Length: 24
Image 1 (tube, rainbow, N blue to C red):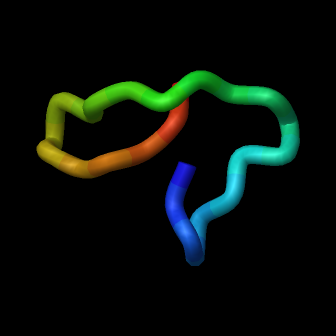
Image 2 (image 1 turned 135 degrees about the vertical axis):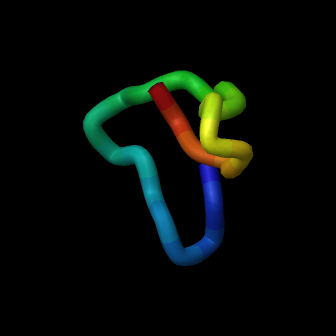
């Protein structure tokens, strides 16, 4: 989802409660 943080496992892009742009 992100340039630095890649989601090769095959996770979907979503918003984290903490307030960050990650994939769950």
